[PDB]
Amino acid sequence: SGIRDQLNIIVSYPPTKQLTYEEQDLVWKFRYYLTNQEKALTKFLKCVNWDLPQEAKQALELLGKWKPMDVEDSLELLSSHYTNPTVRRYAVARLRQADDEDLLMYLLQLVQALKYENFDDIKNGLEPLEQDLCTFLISRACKNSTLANYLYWYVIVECEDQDTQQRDPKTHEMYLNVMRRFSQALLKGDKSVRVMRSLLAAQQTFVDRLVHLMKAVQRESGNRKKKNERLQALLGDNEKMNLSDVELIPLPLEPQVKIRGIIPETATLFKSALMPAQLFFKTEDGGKYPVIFKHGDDLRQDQLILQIISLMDKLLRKENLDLKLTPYKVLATSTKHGFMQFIQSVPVAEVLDTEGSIQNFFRKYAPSENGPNGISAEVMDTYVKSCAGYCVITYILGVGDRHLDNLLLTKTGKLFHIDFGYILGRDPKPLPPPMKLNKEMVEGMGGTQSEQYQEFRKQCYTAFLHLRRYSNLILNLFSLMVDANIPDIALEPDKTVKKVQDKFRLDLSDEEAVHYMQSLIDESVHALF
Ligand SMILES: Nc1ncc(-c2ccnc(Nc3ccncc3)n2)c(CC2CC2)n1
């Protein structure tokens, strides 16, 4: 039997690779032989004409007898492609074997995946073991405060979405029903479950008041110094604003952190057009949590990229590879405003302007005599690792608008990227390089002939080989985002996944891919001359 060779190629395919008429009839011919292969069920379900009552009936029979698929593959079954109630329930049942830690990593996409669900089932669950996506998400949210906090904010922003409201009123109403269903489930739950609902309410009003505070500061006609004094004044008045002192509510940005209020004196506005605020949150244990509060911007694209960077960091750490990345938290509280976790760092542009180079900066704040080029071995290892991680991650996500004001550096050697306005190949200038690696980074690791540069390339291959192994999960997650109001996705929804897939070079073998990665680093470093 030599047919199993061509058959195994079809099974190993990416989730978004369309099966040809020939491949389709080959999978449908050998269905029963494939019931022992789990990664095959995925390929089997896309051969079925679900509009044919006889064909669907036999397929649902095979589903039952089939070796259950991994959580990662069940995500495909929740995309717009499947409408079969039984296939969608099967996906929920497989997603259920995953723990809350993995579930949270997928929550952003699953809230999107609700627009592919039965809208009538969602509405009818409202008061006048085999759950749908809505029922499952609420079920898990009632048992986990962290899960419930993100479910609240991810859904509220979709309700608030005015573009969805006018261009698709059916979808907007479904999300209001998802919110109503969640609120209903919380009020019907235990003593612990019912307090969760008032905590979400408290956070909502805190955000509402914080929004109002931002608008009140702009009433002050004066300069930034006068605007800052205005911000600090209003923040001190807890009778009026009620933001310096509040009952310990979870921080929307990181719900595991409970807060007492915002320190009024250390609160300032950033020198930028939209003037976002830098706010220090008093935690329950007397600590400080710096946040950026942005009003007049849609953080949903940055929220998606940072959620993917977080997943890629977790996947790499799981493979015993800590590339010292900065997956800072981003939570959108509206389509008009949101939070970002503040990381203490210096933009690479300010590094050059004040110290001349990265290596000078490193020598100033972290010197070591026997260390490479007079810099600490720990700081240098951190920098080489982070450069590598970000080089591969930005390449995969096709991050544009890379300039030295949105490349940040820490004194501990951590290098990270911010502001993901241009993603999936888009850039302000035409013909962008596929590898975003500038001369400043190369010079920081001691030039193209250093041992650090060789380690950097090595780390790049490792990271690229590890992330390619997780392409199925990443591509499934991006596939659930196709119809989301994410600017760089909404431009070409139908072409989005393919833009990510091509970066993996899944056509090449592990050895060929390392060759491609080493040449791509070569050609980009070459172009810098
Ligand atoms: N769009 C955007 N995306 C991310 C960040 C961000 C996120 C996390 N940490 C930091 N840190 C710094 C940044 C600039 N200078 C020092 C630290 N910045 C920022 C910078 C804030 C001025 C608005 N903007």
Image (tube, rainbow, N blue to C red):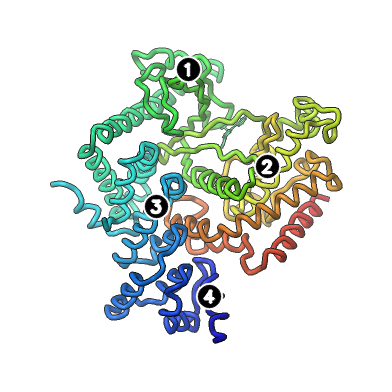
Q: Amino acid at mark 4?
A: Ile
Crowd around label 1: few <14 · some 14–19 · many ≥20 (10 Å): few
Read off the residue under disc 1: 286
- Residue in front for this viewpoint, 161 or 12: 12
Mark earlier in primary sequence (2, 1): 1
Name the residue located 55 percent from the left edge and 46 percent from the top edge. 314
Quadrant of the image where one finds ligand 1: top right
Secondary element at image label 1: loop
Which amino acid type is shown beneath numbered disc 2? Ser
Q: Is residue 60 above or below residue 157?
A: below
Instruction: Answer with left or right where residue 147 lies relative to residue 462.
Output: left
Q: Secondary structure at mark 4?
A: helix
Numbered disc in front, either 3 or 4: 4
- Reading the image, the residue beneath label 2 is 386
Crowding near pointer 2: few (<14 within 10 Å), some, many (20+)?
many
User: Would you say the beta carbon of the disc 3 residue lies within 8 angstroms of ligand 1?
Assistant: no
Mark with earlier residue (3, 2): 3
Location of residue 419 (image quadrant):
top right
**283, above or below 254, in the image:** above
Q: Is mark 4 within 8 Å of ligand 1?
A: no
Label 2 SS:
helix
Residue at 28% over, 76% down: 57
Discs 4, 1 touching: Cβ within 8 Å: no
Viewer-nearest residue: 527 or 320: 320
- Mark 3 lies on residue: 110
Q: CA distance from mark 3 to mark 1?
A: 36 Å
Which residue is tagged 4?
10
